[PDB]
Image 1 (cartoon, protein in one colour):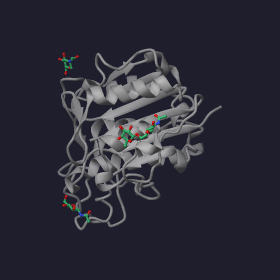
Image 2: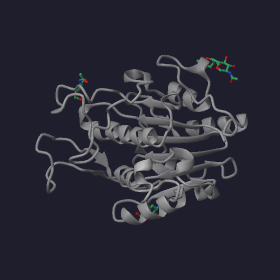
Image 3: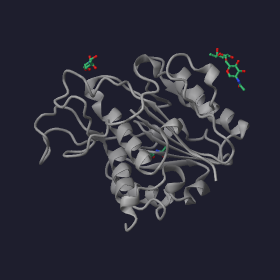
Image 4: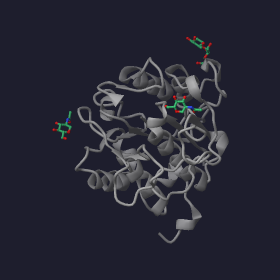
Length: 275
Ligand SMILES: *[C@@H]1O[C@H](CO[C@@H]2O[C@@H](C)[C@@H](O)[C@@H](O)[C@@H]2O)[C@@H](O)[C@H](O)[C@H]1NC(C)=O
Ligand SMILES: *[C@@H]1O[C@H](CO)[C@@H](O)[C@H](O)[C@H]1NC(C)=O
Ligand SMILES: *[C@@H]1O[C@H](CO)[C@@H](O)[C@H](O)[C@H]1NC(C)=O
């Protein structure tokens, strides 16, 4: 019962920030393969990578060496300077009349729907937007409190790839409104980039990192398993263990929500039914 929705947002701009847009495009491919529909996936990506004069492969974005083109077919709801706090927060709330610029696609969800939000690109108490102002912890949590008050969702999972990512939720995110959050790092740690030049077996055409460590770890995990048999809690434990040497994967909010299979939010790719 209900519909799966998602909001994917890369909070940065500039070719050196290739990884944030590659991470978000990779998440789109997982949702598309799982049967989540484009009308229910709101994408915020600056869109300055695929056709950049510096990109050695125009029209292509990869999130791993030798990987597939993750840019192919990704919707463009909010690009360029339309990625900002006003539009990101109105999209989460689901109020089309509060969007200023962009497609107007928002989470106009119903009570049995599921929501998955993934943000990639931070400092204590804030995460980036392509231009100032940045998004502050209190303002993001206040929007989540407004969304909970409307009652227009069954449960929500929010994944954040950023430095000090846990600072967006620590001591603020409510625990009884069906919102579970997972962060690449805790409130006082930075997060790591990965797939950078100068590593064994790396495409010689690139001078930028292709992904972020926590992101490619959870994204590649989604690609390799039947999401009906892996829960959010099992992914938390697996990814937390895998990257313990770099940062402390952290969880906040309504922890029992993580008993849900990942397919509740992402669907599942029939090619991995045996895995
Ligand atoms: C949906 O949003 C409407 C527009 O909000 C107004 O415009 C935005 C851009 C901001 O300036 C905001 O402060 C304004 O209030 C509201 O008129 C409307 O009541 C909202 N609907 C619901 C159900 O919340
Ligand atoms: C390409 O990347 C450069 C470096 O960040 C940026 O200044 C420029 O705006 C981008 N151009 C396009 C066409 O996306
Ligand atoms: C964050 O993780 C580090 C370990 O890398 C730990 O020393 C620190 O106490 C943690 N901070 C919080 C607020 O939990």
